[PDB]
Amino acid sequence: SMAEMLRRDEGLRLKVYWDTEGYPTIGIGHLIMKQPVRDMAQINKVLSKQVGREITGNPGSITMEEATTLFERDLADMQRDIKSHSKVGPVWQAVNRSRQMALENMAFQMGVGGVAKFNTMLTAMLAGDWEKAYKAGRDSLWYQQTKGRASRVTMIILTGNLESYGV
Amino acid sequence: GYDKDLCEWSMTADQTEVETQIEADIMNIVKRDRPEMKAEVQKQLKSGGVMQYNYVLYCDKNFNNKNIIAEVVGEL
Ligand SMILES: [Cl-]
């Protein structure tokens, strides 16, 4: 499942932390605000609307059930966007569920708009040229900067299965 | 790996304390198993983040922490 896959790649927090860009984050890679804000009154105010009840704490905390609910909504939002995207969508519709997961994993990390920048990789996937698609994914700055995750994800694109995640 | 105390602590404690523990645990395995990979691992932790490894290291009985090097830098 995407839950198991992204729990592995994103980790699991019940208290706010800040990502590599300085953005407040919680749960399974749930971005609270795309701003380098540390003020906990403001972070908790936004997170309260996202979770649906008043968040408290410095930093704010959620329960495990809330983290799962945020993830399910984040996953659904990303899946909505990837399927309707004029460049990524056609590729997602043309590959098997495992390779769909790889694309969804990337979109969860970088946004569907980030995935759309992988022109060579996407073109190769539409052609079934998996070695070319794999090499294009591994030639990227994304691979340079999150190499372990990019390795596991591009291995899916190459092999068409999830064994790089132990499945 | 699964560690009852570190699992929940890593989910809830202040980020700075948790990242110090994660980074120390990773770097200890690197030094034992693939010491030449220290600079590559440090580079990946800076560019890619540290916090995300809390789940596989402390919350997942099915993940063997000897594999955390490949988790950070990729297979082989
Ligand atoms: Cl070990």
Image (cartoon, rainbow, N blue to C red):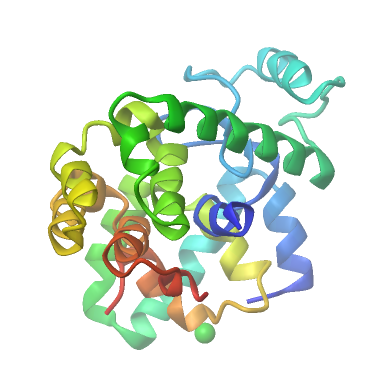
Which residue is pictured at 47% across the width and 83% down the height?
B66
From the viewer's perspective, tell me whether residue B36 is left or right of residue A90: left
Quarter of the C terminus of chain B within the rendering: bottom left
Measured from the top left, where is residue A107 in percent x and y? Answer: 41, 38
Task: Give left or right: position of B34 versus A162.
Answer: left
Q: Nearer the viewer, residue A88 or A62?
A: A88
Seen from the viewer's position, the closer of residues A55 and A154 is: A154
Q: Name the residue furthest right.
A: A53
Say which quadrant the N terminus of chain B sits in: bottom right
Asked if B48 appears above or below A76 in the picture, the reply is: below
Note whether B45 is above or below B24 in the view shown: above
What residue lies at 23% left-to-right and 46% top-to-bottom? A126
Residue appearing at x 54%, y 18% in the figure: A37
Q: Number of labelled discs?
A: 0
Q: Position of residue B27 (x, y in %)?
A: 40, 71
A107 in relation to B74, above or below: above
**The quadrant where residue A61 appears:** top right
Q: Position of residue A49 (x, y in %)?
A: 76, 16
User: Which residue is located at x 58 percent, y 67 percent?
Assistant: B56
B47 left or right of B9? left
